[PDB]
Amino acid sequence: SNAILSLSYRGGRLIDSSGYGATMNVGSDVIFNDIGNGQFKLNNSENSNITAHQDNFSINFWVRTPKYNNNDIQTYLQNEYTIISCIKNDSGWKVSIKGNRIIWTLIDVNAKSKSIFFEYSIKDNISDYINKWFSITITNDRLGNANIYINGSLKKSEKILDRINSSNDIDFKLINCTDTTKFVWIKDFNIFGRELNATEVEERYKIQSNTLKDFWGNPLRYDTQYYLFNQGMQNIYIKYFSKASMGETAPRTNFNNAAINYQNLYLGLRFIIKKASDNIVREGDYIYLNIDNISDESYRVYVLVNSKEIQTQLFLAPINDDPTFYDVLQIKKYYEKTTYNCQILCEKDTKTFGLFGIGKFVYDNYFCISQWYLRRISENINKLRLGCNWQFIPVDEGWTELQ
């Protein structure tokens, strides 16, 4: 139904947008930003805290938690710490994190507890969860079922048990975390006074998602260094091929040990998005793609305008005024609009050159532009043809790499 409580960071202050007038107490070691409305970071200190002073309800919020430290994996796996709690006389509810698990716990007046959790892999080459914003929704009823939804989709649902106390305070704070460097990002925290159904959860997800985002789920920005990720070919990156003035694919390198495995992200061409015509890139903007790690001089992505082929290799070159090439691009989000993917179009202007992708040429796979990606092969084509879907990866503190 209607939010009992909703945290928003409006104009320098954390408030309750609920209209229920919750009063907020904020420690001195909390970091805020005004992205969306907005975001806060809990560090591992007693001074990094927020208190909201206020059998069927729902909890919804998005969370961003940092990648494990390769050399501190047993701490990551074994240390469960509370992040959000509503407890009184040892009874109530808490949200906790234990490594790659997010955990919901109900505790009765006798200290008898039962938990439900969501676990994501820490062995996949590419993760939709590690260090990335993702939405969680927990519902609970009197039947009684507890459900965990992740990114709008039901992931778990279990029963069931004495009485569970209700508290006037909700504490946002790391409890029992043993890594002094730990932090957690939270946004869009909401409480509902009823059990939201599967349809209600999906819709609130789509709503809480026109904004172009980066790989981590934050707004995409101009003048920011980004590595490039391809949704259709996730296990390669784009590398400058000196002999040809092109981008060729290369296999991502990886790291693995006994407990974990991942492919490296900070590889290949490093791009900067420039305004062609604030610093947030919006759907449909006209942009250039600069590349700043090929040499001392700036390079840029060019489209061969006088090609009659279906697909053409993109020309990665020093800045020039050669009219046989064109550098004005448009970043778009044609579909899968809740994801962090985007497409790159070039048009000039009654003439469409296609979308950026990866194509087979005389053979190897090259960073290219192709009309193939605009073909309306079938109504579901966009679910099958993923090579024109890209994400931009900035270096982020929650994801560190060797070398």
Image (cartoon, grey):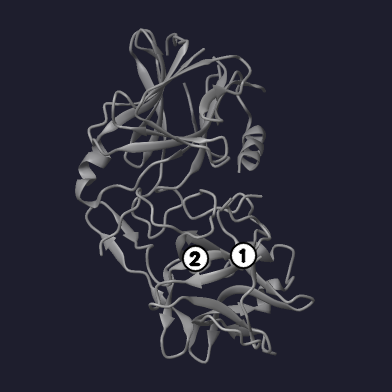
Identified at 41% across, 86% down, the residue is 242
Mark linked to residue 272: 2
Residue shown at 70% from the left, 62% from the top: 380
Amino acid residing under circle 1:
Gln
Residue 144 point in image, percent of width and height: 53, 19
Tell me: 225 left or right of 9.
Answer: left
Q: How far apart are marks 2 and 1 (CA)?
A: 16 Å
> Which of pointers 2 and 1 indicates the residue nearer the eye?
2
The quarter of the image holding the N terminus is: top right
Other-residue count near label 1 (Cα within 10 Å), few / some / many at <14 / 14–19 / ≥20: many
User: Which type of secondary structure does the marked residue at label 1 adopt?
Assistant: strand
Q: Where 286 sits versus 40, above or below?
A: below
Give the vertical position of 275 relative to 317 (above or below).
above
Between 212 and 29, which is closer to the camera in this rendering?
29
Indicate the amino acid at tag 2.
Ile
Where residue 90 sits, quadrant-wise, is top left
Q: Where, quadrant-wise, is the C terminus in this rendering?
A: bottom left
Q: Identify the mark nearer the N-term, 2 or 1.
A: 2
Give residue 115's position: percent from left, percent from top.
Answer: 39, 26
The answer to whether residue 224 is left or right of residue 182 is right
Q: Residue 343 carries which label?
A: 1
Q: In this view, does 50 lie above or below 333?
A: above
> Which element is circle 2 on?
strand
Q: Position of residue 127 (x, y in %)?
A: 42, 54
